[PDB]
Length: 104
Length: 104
Ligand SMILES: [As]
Ligand SMILES: [As]
Ligand SMILES: [As]
Ligand SMILES: [As]
Image (cartoon, each protein chain N blue to C red):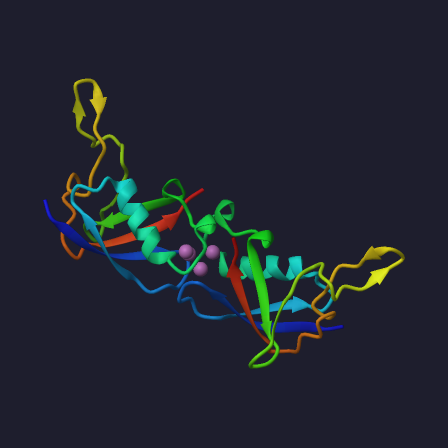
């Protein structure tokens, strides 16, 4: 378990990508929080998108992208409860290209 | 009364400025709506900032900027009611540089 430096683009407008450091053990909500803190640092917090307002997609291949969520159908189920997905759960590599998107 | 092409920056992230056409007779809410439509075209409408979430500032001089609102203390008062400020009310020139900002 180590830190991961992610190259995140925020899709929808022509912003530059940002390098964001997250932890393998961060839940993907926490990963989103860190990304939003990085992108929205110069804006009042009352106006930031929330974790629930955005998807985070990992471009694993040219043809395969995986939407990274806390809970989904790849989540470990333990003693009758789902466990939260972490960055390490999806085996996200160092320098991975991620895209963040506002959703309906 | 004519159209005005405004050079609008959206401050807070490193987006390029956009040229936005507004009418002299547009209320500043309508001007904001047109600007948000231009900047947020590729994002779901449920996630756009609203007119009330942003200020629009006109850099009239190097040292003077005026926040452009529908109603303020420069508004014409007629028969006991304030009249909505328009783009023409502030005498905004063609090719004017404006900045839009998210507010608390
Ligand atoms: As955006
Ligand atoms: As932001
Ligand atoms: As912004
Ligand atoms: As937008």
